[PDB]
Length: 315
Length: 292
Ligand SMILES: Nc1nc2c(c(=O)[nH]1)N(C=O)[C@@H](CNc1ccc(C(=O)N[C@@H](CCC(=O)O)C(=O)O)cc1)CN2
Ligand SMILES: O=c1[nH]c(=O)n([C@H]2C[C@H](O)[C@@H](COP(=O)(O)O)O2)cc1F
Image (cartoon, rainbow over all chains, first blue to last red; front, side, top):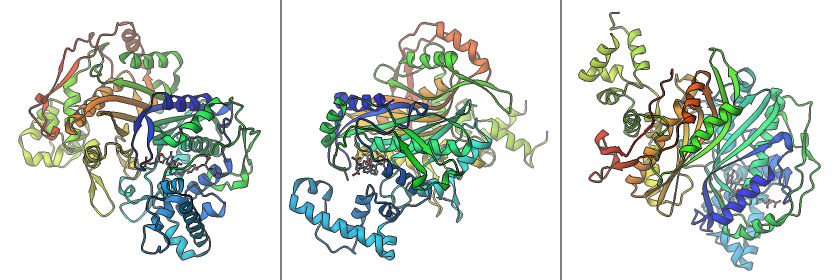
C-alpha cells in the first residue's frame, strides 16, 4: 500500500534517532522495518510525488544485462549514478580540473562552486559518452549489482549467473526455500563504489502467484526507497511473465531506514498530499525472457501523480 | 515480546498455506515476517515451553571460535552436528561394521582421528570467520565487523553473510541463517537476522536465543549496551505434525523472560566458555515433545 511507505516516512520523522552518516549530512533513522505491497492492487509507483519510471526502467535493464559502466545509463539519459563515478574520477591522477573535495555539500553552500562543478561534471559526462578508453576507465563503478546478479566470480576462473539460475529454479522447483539472490560479495565490497544497499532478495510461490522479499541494509527514504520499490516490483512482474505466474506481494525489509535531514521538509510536504491510485503496468507479451526486454517494452499507464518534490542527493 | 512469537504460530494456523512436497512432508507457511525483541526487557528464552540453553550456547560459542570440528561440541555434550560426521566415517576405509558411542569416544581422545573425522566442511564457523577469496585468502567478516563497530559505530555496512552462491549448490545443509546486520545508536547494539527458511515450532525458539546471545556477546566485546534483536523471515513454515504442539503452547500464559548474566572478569568473549554464560530467573512451562 502507498500508505505503508508514507507511514514509514512519518515514523522516521516522528521517532527517528538523529545519526551521523558516512556522508556527514545527518540523518533520522530506525533499525528494522517491513512493508508489503500487493501487486494485484496496482503497480507501486508513488502517487504522492512524481517518480520517473523511465529512469527506474533503464537502471533495472542496466542491472539485468550485467553492466556496471554508467555509459549505458548516460545513453538513455539517466544521471542517477554519476556522482560516484565522478568522485572516483576527481580523486584519480588523471583529473586536473578545479578542486572537488567534498563537492556533495559544497554545491549546496557556494553558488560559484556549483558552476565550477556543473562544468566539470558536464565534461565528465561527454568524455564518458564519446571516448571509449575514458568510458572504460571512468564509467566503471566496480562489481556492483549487475556483476553479482549475472557474473559472480568463482575461485576457479569462472562465474555464477545468479539471476538466471533463480528464474530457472522458479520454473522447475517453485517450492524451493533457496530461491535467493545476493549482491553481498565480501570479497568485492571494498572495491565497489557503494556496497549493495538492496543487498539480497528471495522468491516465493503459492497458488500460481510469485512473491518477492528484498533485504535492504540501508534505505534513503525520500529519494532512495521510491526507486527501489518500483525497481523490485518491475523485476517481480518481469519474472512472473517469463515463468508464467501471477503476481503476489513485494515485501520490503529494511535495516537502517533513514531520512536525510535536508529531506525533512520534502517528506513533510509529501505527507500533506492525498494518496491517489497506483497505475497499471503493461508488458510486451511477445517477449519471452527477463533478459529480452528493452525500454520500449515496459510501460506504466494511468499514472497521475502530484508534482515532483526536488531534494539533494547525499554523496 | 514473547507474545510477538506466539502471534506468528497463531497466524500460521489461521491463514498459513498448505504444501506437500517430494518427501511427503506437509507444511503451513507464510512469506515475510518481522519480530522484535527488546533485550532490555529480558533475554528471549521462550517461557511457554522449556528451551534448553546449554546446546544453544555451546553451538554459538563453537560458531564464534571459527571451529568447524565437532570435538568442541562433543567435549560439551552437544550432539546437534554428529550426523554428517558419523555418516562420512561409516563410508570410509577404516570401519569394521552402539557404534555411534565408539566414534564419539574416538573423536574425543585421539587428536589424529579428529582432524580427520570430526571435520564438517562449509558451515557457520567457516562462513563467519573464514570466507575464501579467489586468491586463497580468507575474510574474517565477524572480526572486521567487530573492528567496524569499535571505530565506526555509525556505519551502515555492519554485515555478516553466510550465503555464497558458488558453495550453496554443492553443500548438504545450505544455511538457514542467511545474513545479519548490526546497527549502533545511543550506546546500544542492535541486530537484525534475515532467515530464509524458518521451522516455526522447533527452529524459531532456538534461533531467537542464539542471535540474542550473539548480540549480547558482541555488545560485551565492543563494550556497549544491548538494544533490540529484529528477526526477519523469508519462508516461515509450521510442520503439519507440529500443529497440536502449537495449539498447546498457545493456551499457556506468558511469564517474564529470564536475565542473562555474563562474567565480567573476562575481557574478550573469544576466551568465553560454558561457565561464563548463565541464565538467572528462568521459570518456563514444561517441555512440549515433538518429532524432529
Ligand atoms: N544517498 C543515496 N545514495 C545512493 C542511493 C540513494 O538512494 N541514496 N541509491 C539508491 O538507489 C543509488 C543511486 N540511486 C538514486 C536514486 C534516485 C536518485 C534521484 O536523485 N532521484 C531524483 C531525481 C530524478 C530526476 O532528476 O529526474 C528524484 O526522483 O527526486 C538518485 C540516485 C546509489 N547511491
Ligand atoms: O539501491 C540503493 N538504495 C539506496 O537507498 N541507497 C542509499 C542508502 C544510503 O542512503 C546510501 C548508502 O550509503 P551507505 O553505504 O553508507 O549506507 O545509499 C543506495 C543504493 F545503492
